[PDB]
Image (spheres, coloured by chain):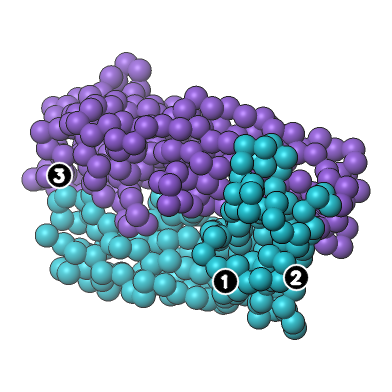
Amino acid sequence: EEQLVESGGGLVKPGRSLRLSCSASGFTLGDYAVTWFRQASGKEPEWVGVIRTKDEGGTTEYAASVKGRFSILRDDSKSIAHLQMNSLKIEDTAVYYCTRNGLRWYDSSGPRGWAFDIWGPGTLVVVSSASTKGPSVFPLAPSSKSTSGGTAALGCLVKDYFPEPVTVSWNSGALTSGVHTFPAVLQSSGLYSLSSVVTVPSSSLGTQTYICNVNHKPSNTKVDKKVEPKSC
Amino acid sequence: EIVMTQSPATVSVSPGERATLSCRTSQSVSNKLAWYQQKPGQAPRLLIYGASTRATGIPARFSGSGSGTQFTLTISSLQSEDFAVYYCQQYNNWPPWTFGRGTKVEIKRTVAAPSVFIFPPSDEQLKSGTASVVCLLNNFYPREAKVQWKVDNALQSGNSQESVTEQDSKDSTYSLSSTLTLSKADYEKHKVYACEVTHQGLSSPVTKSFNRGEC
């Protein structure tokens, strides 16, 4: 099964640089143009740049907003490509994608168009002068106050971190049913805060271990907090 | 250049009914038109190419049609998993790397009252000087809801924040999280912490509360 994965996003200061990587598995990346997109603020994907195949000269083109600052490289032997970002600006903050152009057509004049049939999951790049800060993780304890009809709710409060994102899973990923991880909200402190909750049978609170696995890569924070029933 | 215009920006279709999305190109692109689906927290996925050809592993209830400048994505018997933003993209005229602004499909399901849960602050947090009280509205529909924080029956104003999930991929509901935040000192000055929830699915407002030092 063919797939792409971006890596390397994180916090970077204005004027600094950052390298993203795009890794292909299950196909020969060198058969394809690698096109970089970015997406912010709930808008549509936006073209960043492309590098053509070796066959087409292996050359690059860039959006006007990044020309002169970004550069694309590819290593066909390892089915990988990179986006090198120099002189970063706050407006560069976005989720970056790489894509393969599996669909192509040509006439006598050359390429006419592409469609992008594989995308990576994305990697978030945050350009800010604010300093990174790991979250505090507090349990949201289940109690008669969070139980409804034989169902109980419990969770984790991930408070006061910067920048996005944090990931949250339950029991190392074995618990997925009934989980709601909420979008982070930006507090007036400029720090983020989010909650993750899961509903389970009341009858399991006395016997089943529930641990939320919180990961905040920008700050090298990993937390696995066990959530303990309260008795009220 | 070739501009993609997508209409409407938002569409609300009941489950199992038919969704119709419009893409219009500022000039003719023949049938070189692709549709993409982007679900919350995910990359886009290729849906249709050639205006009417479904990608690998795309269910049959998705279909596209049109040529020239008017194109249509149709989703028959809409499923809860179809909640996403949908993008069109022409590739008849170089370059191909432009998308329209997208159409969001939201699922108009039946009314669902929320389940309401309350969480007291943790000892860990309180020792550090702060108390976050969290109120949970789980799996309701429609999205509008009123969350009312009361402390010793005093309606609270200006000290809470909330966020809402995207419409759930399995049952098309929303869940809502409201955090009330106080200093330890203010927290320890009062007894009853309550949230009051009003929603279209509730025949009367629902209250969950606790007394500090009870949990």
Residue at image point 67% right, 59% down: B135
Circle 2 SS class: strand
Foreground label between 3 and 2: 2
Q: Are marks 3 and 2 in contact (CB under 8 Å)?
A: no
Residues under labels 3 and 2: Cα distance? 52 Å
Residues under labels 2 and 1: Cα distance? 19 Å
Report in which chain the residue with disc 3 lies: A
Residue A154's place in the image compared with B180, above or below, is above
Residue sitting nearer the eye, A69 or B84: A69
Pointer 1 residue = B143
Residue A75: % across, % down? 28, 19
Amino acid type at image mark 1: Arg
Amino acid type at image mark 2: Thr
Q: Residue furthest left?
A: A109
Q: Quadrant of the N terminus of chain B?
A: bottom left
Foreground label between 2 and 1: 2
Chain A: its colour in the image is: purple
Q: Is residue A191 toward the left or the right of residue B156 in the image? A: left
Residue A43: % across, % down? 33, 57
Q: Which mark is residue A65?
A: 3
